[PDB]
Image: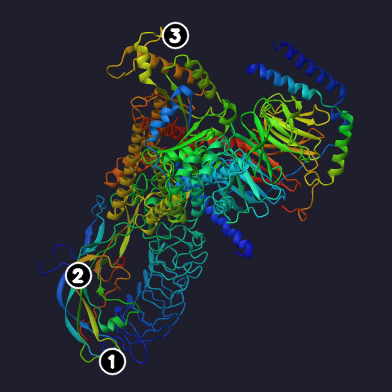
Amino acid sequence: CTLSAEDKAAVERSKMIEKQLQKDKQVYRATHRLLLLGADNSGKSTIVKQMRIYHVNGYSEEECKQYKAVVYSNTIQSIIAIIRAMGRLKIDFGDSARADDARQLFVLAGAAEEGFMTAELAGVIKRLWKDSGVQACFNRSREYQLNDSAAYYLNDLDRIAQPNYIPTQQDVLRTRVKTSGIFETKFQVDKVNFHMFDVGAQRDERRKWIQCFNDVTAIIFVVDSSDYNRLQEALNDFKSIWNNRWLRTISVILFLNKQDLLAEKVLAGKSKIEDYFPEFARYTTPEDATPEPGEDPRVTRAKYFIRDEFLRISTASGDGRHYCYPHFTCSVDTENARRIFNDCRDIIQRMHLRQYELL
Amino acid sequence: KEPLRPRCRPINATLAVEKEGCPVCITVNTTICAGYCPTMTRVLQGVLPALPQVVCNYRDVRFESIRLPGCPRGVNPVVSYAVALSCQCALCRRSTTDCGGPKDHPLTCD
Amino acid sequence: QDCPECTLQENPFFSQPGAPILQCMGCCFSRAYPTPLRSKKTMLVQKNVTSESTCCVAKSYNRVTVMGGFKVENHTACHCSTCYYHKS
Amino acid sequence: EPCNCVPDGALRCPGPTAGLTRLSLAYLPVKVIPSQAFRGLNEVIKIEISQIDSLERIEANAFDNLLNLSEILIQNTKNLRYIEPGAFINLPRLKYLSICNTGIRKFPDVTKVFSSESNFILEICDNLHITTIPGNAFQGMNNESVTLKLYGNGFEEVQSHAFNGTTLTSLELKENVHLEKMHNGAFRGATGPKTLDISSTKLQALPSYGLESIQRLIATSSYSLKKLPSRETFVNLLEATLTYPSHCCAFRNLPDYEYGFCLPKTPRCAPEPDAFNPCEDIMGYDFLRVLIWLINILAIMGNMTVLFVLLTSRYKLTVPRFLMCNLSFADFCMGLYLLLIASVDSQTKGQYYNHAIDWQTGSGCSTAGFFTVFASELSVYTLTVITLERWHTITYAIHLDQKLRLRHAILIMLGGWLFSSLIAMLPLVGVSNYMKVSICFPMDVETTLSQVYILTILILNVVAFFIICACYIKIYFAVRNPELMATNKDTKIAKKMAILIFTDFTCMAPISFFAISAAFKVPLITVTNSKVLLVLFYPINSCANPFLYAIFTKTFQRDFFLLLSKFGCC
Amino acid sequence: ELDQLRQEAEQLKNQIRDARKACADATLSQITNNIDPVGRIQMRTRRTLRGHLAKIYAMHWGTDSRLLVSASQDGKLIIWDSYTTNKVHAIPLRSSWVMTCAYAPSGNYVACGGLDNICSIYNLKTREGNVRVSRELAGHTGYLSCCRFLDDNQIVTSSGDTTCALWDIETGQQTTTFTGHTGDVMSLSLAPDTRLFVSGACDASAKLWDVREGMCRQTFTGHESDINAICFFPNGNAFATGSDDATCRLFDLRADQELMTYSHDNIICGITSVSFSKSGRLLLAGYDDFNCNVWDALKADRAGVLAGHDNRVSCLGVTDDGMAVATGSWDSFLKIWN
Amino acid sequence: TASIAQARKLVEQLKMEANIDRIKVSKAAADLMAYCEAHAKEDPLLTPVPASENPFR
């Protein structure tokens, strides 16, 4: 076609952007989005910890670049905050030498970089941190807006200044550990990209943010079976999410964590579930139950009663559109990955069959 | 067969072979289908179709060629003759030959 | 052979009692030979065989009456001169 | 060369003034025959003119007042390019007059003979130079019955009233290559002929009138005779021969020397119709005339509705949508072929035999057979590829990366289309002629190659069905679980799979078995019996696939509702 | 004991309601009955860009009515040009989810935020060309809801923890805090006068805040359900807000009471977007359904029906000069109407 | 306690909001009508324009 030089350059840029976004989409479609819900005492932290040992290759090229950029930005912000605290303190504690002050000023001016921190800035920051006055000012201004990891960044600034730095996963989490509300994590099962969204540390108003999560493939719900009293709140939350208009089309997976704790608690013979749930006395063990050898009958009966109640509340409406996949949860085994992969495969197959007129 | 009223069988007759472009006439031995076959005429007319009469003729023939001695130039000096090993009496096709009234023409070169 | 010669014979099925029907038939011989150069040039169409056909036919016939009212002719003489229905 | 003929044969003259019992002109070097040169002789009984190459022309009134003469034979006219009219006249006792191997371009007049013989036979042959038969040429030739045998006549056409005022016994016109066309008024005044021979005549059609008195007819090797007159017209017909085996069945239905007055009770014709071409119309039963129409109407309506729904969809195209569109197009093609066959049957309703040759020899039958093969092959390929892709996307549902896309499916669809086109066009090349069966089906199994091809096609269809069944069984096994299993969902899936597999099993198993049996040269059923299967079992897919696939689909229903709302029928 | 405080609050509310009723005589519909209602307006699509990959969450128009910024929940931030319908640059984000967008009057800075509490600021005039985070405005205890570039130096943002704060790019700290509010804040709007702005709360109570005052000025509770969108009259003397009950209401800074109710018996889905015309004579709003409608403020009657989107309208925007109006749906296709 | 502080803050906010002034609705109605009439001529959506002058053809 015929176009102007500026028009040709714009078309070339648009084509490059289109190619880049197509490449990003190629990977995006292969990733399955999953959302995790659980109470503070539900043990979700333990659940995520178990899968944390099997992260997705530890790190990725794009992930590594993003982590390096975040670390550089955090270091620059910490240096700027330290300089501001030193300059605004009661005593104008300056650098030991005018060269250090000039280097700090240049770094502050150079903080406008696009994510890459020059080695000179890192060296200047490290030299400034070695000064006794700078350390004293930082200690006296620990209550300022300086990042909590400022000391760690200063101590590790020597390694950060080296090219091709590879920060540890714990270090990256600490750098990104804040009041974000999202705890992203990556893990691979059967060479399949799996995402998990830990949501919390925010207002308990599910009517405001669950709306956008209608595209999630499945929602994981985790509740601690040990706490008999917490069941009522858990039951109410499950009922509310199940009846949610936006989420009334996505299946859920239930994990009954703290199985060992529940077994230990019921071993005392207190039987506090009866008071909370009077129907437990009239409940009976299902004929399809397959308890493991050596398990106390009371614990298995209670677990199966809880599972039956969860199924009954879920089957109130919209059973065909979306199902429920409860599983006994114990943070002592790695079989959870296989169970969740099987559940995802089953729900994907059911969804595919729904549109093929086979169900 | 019997010496009298022989059937339609080949005989060692002599036939003259010549071409328009070759004035030389050459006579060689050839098999000629001659004899007698049963024939009859319908006893009624105007009711049933006339019954065809079988005439002795040759059923299978073989092509034989002989050298042409000094035939005139401008034409192919090839002479073809038909030799029949078996003979039978049957109707003669219109395009097969010119079967008709007897002629008793000589079989030699005039 | 034993084929009868060219002479009148009784009708196999048209010979009413008291008046046999005469039919003409025979075993007249025929001769044929390959067409010579003169014969070939005497035919407008291409012919590679020449045959002479002689058949026994009734010289004359009379008027006779057959059973059922059918009109038939009774032969009075037989001779081998030519053929009429030989061509097909 | 020297000759021993009685006539002088000198000075380019025949020397007719010679006393001889049987005049002959063999090897006679005579080119001009003097007019009235035969006078003054009475001992001659027969006159023969044969082996006369020098003959070029004959003077008029050559044979006049030849009372003694009764038979005249003329043959071997090498250069007889012209004959003076009126050569034969005043022959009360004339019996036979034969003229053969004559190159005369003008028809010799014979009305002046005025023969009074009881039976007069006239034979004309090798009249290549003859242009046409002059009108009223045979009128007045003989007062009594006269038989004309114009075998191998070169006449281009017959003038009107050619035979008038005469009782013709037989009219033999065999080997009449140039007599393909003739007027219907030739026998306007002839009481007959009783028997006619039009073998090898290549006549386009027979005259409407004059066939009532015809008792026997010969039409051997009459390829051009693709049509026959009315059956009731041949009231007196008793025996005839027809080149086309199908035409012989027309005389099957009704509206030796010792036989005498006795005649056969029913007409006799040969050769009999072939087994592969039974004497019947397209539909052998009365009810099929309506069932076939209803099935075709339903199939075409469903295909049109599905095509309209799919083509007008504004949503993004999907591989299932394209597959459904292709299946709908195949069903539409099959319905169009069935409608064309039904229309052809209706047009030739009650006259199947008359138009059987034209219909089976025209391009219509070939097109119908090609459509029948192509639509079936395309439908089978579409169904099997749909099953295969469903199996693949169910077995590896979690691996979203390994998912079919439109660009990848187009190549496979094009390859399948090319394969189906080649499969359908191979019989048209000559592998298996479609004219063997009147329904335009490749029934030519006599050839080893054709039988092998049919067996290969049947084996391929069987293998495709087996693969589909295996894929469905694998899908059912994978979906089923030992613990996480739902009785209702499992039962529904099993019922759906069973109906889906059976809807094709009880459409393919009988046809496949019949084809396999026919391939081994062991027909279990006749053509008429196979017609019921071909009209009842063949269109099962065209009437079941659309309703069972797109009609019972949420997306199709939504699209139809949206289209209705847009059109105003909300 | 809080009985005395409750009684005093009830008495004050009753007095305020009585004063508002006394000051109010009749609705604007009766006064506007003397003006002929606007006729049917025909809109035809002019541009349609299919380059967007994932669902669209928010969109903001440009001050020059030349470039529009779009955001997606997948994490890709790409800006389009209306004249050429071609993307200019692509901005990756550390947080996939986005719920707000902004475009500075000069177009140099672009900011967006989503469920994650860490807000990011991006520049379109980077020295190296590639876009990158200029600074971070983290520390919020709630998810980001909406953003609007009041100027090139100060930014006012909404937090999910029922708190609104004012941040400075140079300082990167909450200069002003508006925590004195009940319920979350969904959307924010800026009137012609930057001195005062109106914030749309998640509840039925709408509060007006000042940059320097730091406290609410007027409270309106005319809505019957949650409010998800709010727009300001170009003259700045009135504003309109949408509700989940489909009962759109118009409020005036002087009347301090509801003026008109724009609802229909056949309209069940609520209103998620709201926008006014250049003169405010016509109001454009999007409902939870896939069809958008145009409302007449003066006539309070339907103007036309638009069904160019196959999914819910995520957001709607109107250019300052009214050159064109674009609606963003939950699908990957953006429709431009003129 | 927290409840007492919240109640006191709510009472203070209500008192502050109760000190605002009020204006006649008729004056605001007239001003809005005049503004709409003045700005009506500059509304492309309300007033159709030829495609030649429209920059979004």
Callout 1, which amino acid?
Answer: Arg
Rate crowding at label 2 as few (under 14), some (14 to 19) or many (20 or more) other CA atoms within 10 Å.
many
The residue furthest left is B2
C34, E49: nearer the viewer: E49
* Tags 2 and 1 on a common chain: no
- Which residue was labeled with disc 3? A279
Viewer-nearest of labels 3 and 1?
3
What's the CA distance linking mark 2 and mark 1?
43 Å
- Which residue was labeled with disc 1? B73
The answer to whether the residues at label 3 and label 2 have Cβ atoms under 8 Å apart is no
- Quadrant containing the N terminus of chain D in the rendered view: bottom left
Image position of C49 with respect to E60: above or below: below
Callout 2, which amino acid?
Answer: Phe
What's the CA distance linking mark 3 and mark 2?
128 Å
- Which residue was labeled with disc 2? C29
Left or right of D135 in this view: D10: left
Give coordinates of residue F54: x percent, y percent. 76, 53
